Length: 99
Image 1 (cartoon, rainbow, N blue to C red):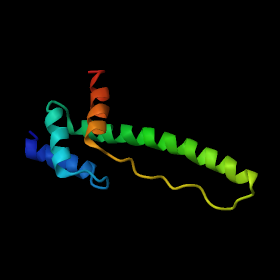
Image 2 (image 1 turned 60 degrees about the horizontal axis):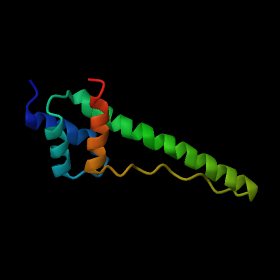
Image 3 (image 1 turned 180 degrees about the vertical axis):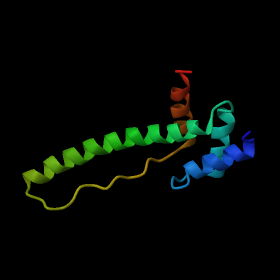
C-alpha cells in the first residue's frame, strides 16, 4: 500500500529536475487520487514527447536558415518545458480519457 505522503514523495522525485513548486506537486497528486505512480511518470513523458517534437522542428528551421548564410554556429539547445500546474493538470486529464 502506497500512502498519500508516499505518492507526493514519488511525484516530487519524478519532477525533481523540473521547476515545480511543492504545492503544485501536492495539487497534482490530490487531483488524480486513484492513479498509480506509473501515471505521473507517463504524464511527464507525454509533456516531454510534445516538447521534443517542437524542438526538432525548431532545429530544422534554424539549420535551413543557417545553410543560406553559410553559418557555422550550432543548433539551438533543447529548453526545459515550463511545467505549470494548469498544463500538468491538462496532460493528466488527457491521460485519463482511455480509462
